[PDB]
Amino acid sequence: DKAMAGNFWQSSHYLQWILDKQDLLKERQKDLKFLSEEEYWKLQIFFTNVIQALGEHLKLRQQVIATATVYFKRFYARYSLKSIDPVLMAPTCVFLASKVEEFGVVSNTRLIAAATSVLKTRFSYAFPKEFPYRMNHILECEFYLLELMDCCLIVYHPYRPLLQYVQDMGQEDMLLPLAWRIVNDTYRTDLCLLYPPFMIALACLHVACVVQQKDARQWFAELSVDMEKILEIIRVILKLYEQWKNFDERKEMATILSKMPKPKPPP
Amino acid sequence: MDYDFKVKLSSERERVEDLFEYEGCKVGRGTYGHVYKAKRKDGKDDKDYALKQIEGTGISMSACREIALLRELKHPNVISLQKVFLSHADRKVWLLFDYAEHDLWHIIKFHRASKANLPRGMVKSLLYQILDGIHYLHANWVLHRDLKPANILVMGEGPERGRVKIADMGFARVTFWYRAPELLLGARHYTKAIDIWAIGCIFAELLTSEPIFHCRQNPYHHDQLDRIFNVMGFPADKDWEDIKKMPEHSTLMKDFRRNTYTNCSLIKYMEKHKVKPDSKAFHLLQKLLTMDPIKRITSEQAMQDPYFLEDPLPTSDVFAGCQIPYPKREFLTEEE
Ligand SMILES: Cc1n[nH]c2ncc(C(=O)N3CCC[C@H]3c3ccc(Cl)cc3)cc12
Image (cartoon, rainbow over all chains, first blue to last red; front, side, top):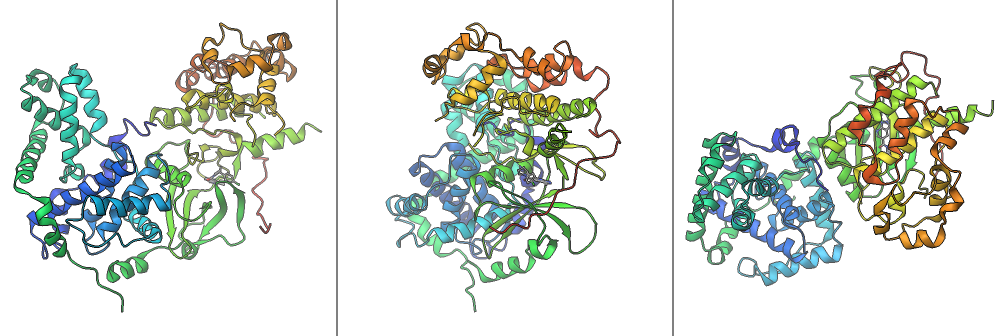
């Protein structure tokens, strides 16, 4: 149930999938011909919400949804938006994540019905037409996803270290709900590709203390961690909430999706 | 799907049939799928490789777990996944491991078959490496969940001669000889204690060449429990106080009386198979085969047992330089 807990520093997550910011930005340039930097971030927020919605429908735990979100991000961290349709990749990532996390194999009917239903009931503003894909497309895409990630399937998330930290504060009731919620929001950014999850947890916990006006400076001082890296993460979280304010997903996304680079068809 | 992306990947993708010769080289068939003894076609080395074609098409639950865990895990006594092939034509997954000529099932069978007509140092060395491998997995919160002689590999001739490799990380969640009594009484979760009972059963079998809880082939299994009590005795109320909380306890009370097993103990069983009850081996065995799972020894505690400080010490090559008498794996020419 707790498989590979405590092994992060020897993990494929740390060793292969903590990426360099400038390398990540360099591979992104092929898509930045078609979209702006602003439009690309908005597009990644959108698909984070799509994966969230899909997982809620299928009644999956947050860790499964989190793992599927990371799978998605890793794919488009390496490849273009034109390579595979993110409308197809999103349910495929959820499908693979539920197997890896031992929730189960989602049935052919349930997965396609979930994808069809969620995009109709919750994302009709972005998608005029119905979910076009069938289960053969999901299984094909699962092979590509698995190959590109180099079979790195175990993913670490900030939730477990966060729970440990608040219990160690003795402030579980007061701080956990907001800190947990701020962790959910960090998946709107590239933070999971750039920082160890325990550092993301501490930054989310710090922002929750500042919001709720809780003095915890002595507790944070006693930690053995590079505080400049934590402050870097905090700045991205604050920047995320300013973009949130200035972003209307519902009004903008149809036009942003139309601007995505299209796949080259066969001869 | 982008065409240039697709053909670029199709060009670069290594295919199992191009890289490895394995036609007619099948060594095993089971619920795991198909295992072959394979060699490199582009002969950079002359090493033996194990190639496993997994059961079914696509990525099964069992396959996901093995791939996910073995991608992360690294320890001398756990088998190493070298490579994964995804065959796009037929949607078949292949896993590449280093090749182990032997395993405990075949080693045990060899000695049991001789009884019509195991060295004690090898028995100790095997047990120590099993515990070491399982301790590493337990330290990473990985349960094997179906430990048995058939999935405890031992390397043959080569640089890893006589090294134990725990295999088959695919148990995602028939005979029950290695299954702890709590599972047989309806335990809902797998645990570390369940892996340790299995190691207890395996250790008894290494000492006697005989499956200790051998039985004729709904978690409640009457005949398997009956065999366990014939060997161990029926547990006292104080031996296992939480037995009352087991879902099948009323069924156990219905079908069994303590008086049936009054003369039964592990001492008397092991005495029949010429294992001394005063031996450090026996006392370690008894701690592994404790009926109450909360009273069962852990893997780390077992590794610190004075049995392993006693002469002879466990060796890294379980055969200890001596000639390997166990035959090599035969190829399977069966159709199916
Ligand atoms: C053989 C061999 N060498 N190296 C290996 N690594 C892994 C595996 C394996 O997947 N499994 C799964 C079940 C128990 C084990 C196994 C052992 C013997 C045979 Cl006949 C077939 C399969 C086999 C080998």
